[PDB]
Amino acid sequence: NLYFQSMPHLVILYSGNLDRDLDMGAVCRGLADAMLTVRDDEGRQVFPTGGTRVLAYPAPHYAIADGGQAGRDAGESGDYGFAYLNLRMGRGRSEAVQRRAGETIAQAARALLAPLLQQRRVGLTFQIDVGAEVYDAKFGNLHALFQKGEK
Amino acid sequence: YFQSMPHLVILYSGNLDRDLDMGAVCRGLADAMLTVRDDEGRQVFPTGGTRVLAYPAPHYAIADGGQAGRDAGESGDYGFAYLNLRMGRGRSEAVQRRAGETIAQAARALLAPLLQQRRVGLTFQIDVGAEVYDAKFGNLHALFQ
Amino acid sequence: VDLGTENLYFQSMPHLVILYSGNLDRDLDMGAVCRGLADAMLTVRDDEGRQVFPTGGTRVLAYPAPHYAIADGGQAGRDAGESGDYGFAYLNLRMGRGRSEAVQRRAGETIAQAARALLAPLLQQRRVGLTFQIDVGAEVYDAKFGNLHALF
Image (cartoon, rainbow over all chains, first blue to last red; front, side):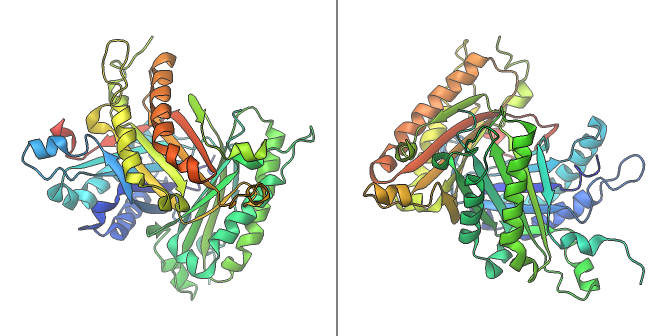
């Protein structure tokens, strides 16, 4: 159903140390922009503009891999980072369309997060989940700005 | 047992904090959850297991980034909140829907003043936990036995 | 029968997220809890003595919530002569598909036992709800694109 696909949310969970030399707000906007470019084989927009949201949360407490040992042993700082990107999309789409959306967003993420790779060792992971919710309600007023109307 | 850990998480844009007491919203939603009853006369979400947690996001991008808002003569500074209830397996579709309607109504009432201040997308979903392992190990439940 | 090697791709991204009430930050160093849990994860072995959770892919994150409501809001605690200032921590491990029930249970037991040990001082001075769940990832798409893996 199109209803099930009307609420795509991408959440970024990342180690707080990444805030040092990257504008995460700009990364959010870049990823949102990337989602909005995705078209199916019929030319339909896969992620509707009105329902798209990207949000990012720096974790104040974290443990990554071995805690730095391998890094320090290799003559590096051992100060690791990570970012985990999760897109929750609606049911009903083919694997090919899911993988197209995945590839497009992943390539955008690679480009936007590229500066991080120069600064430290960083794990970067992106997953797409399909929502299996048993109840849905939309009740905001944002949708009103994306309704059709000739002036 | 699967239903003994009812968990409501709110992910929302940090800009909402200016126009909202999010602690009061959490309390209101928790109160609403405690009112949900099945057709066997039982409280659906146990008091001892009920938790509502809310997280303001410091970084976010919403919809077109503001253009549609500006075209309507507004600021285009959008907000959003996403509410997710993770409940246990083994409940009827009727009970799941009753839970959803009760919580959605509470959310509509609690967030009505916010909708007067900003364009805000508001979404609420109920997921049923599909976990392969569960452990409960706190001392909070002891107060409700 | 455990099918870890057959599902190798899906085994490289185990992450444990902790969502907890912000008041717990007054009671303990949550960073030390994360480290202790990561240490515990790396100890889990399958029936061959192989590491279930790869070191390079192991991630533990903890998020204090600034706004929360727990249980009855303190009444039962105050009635029992306590503060009624409750806490809660919810721990969720997302692991890969294709593992045996026994491997899932071993992972659960090892991590739960570590969590009980690390969070025990909390229980001495506060009423805290503590829940741990393991979910199996059912993602339809993955991408791995960091530079951390090279060290491992």
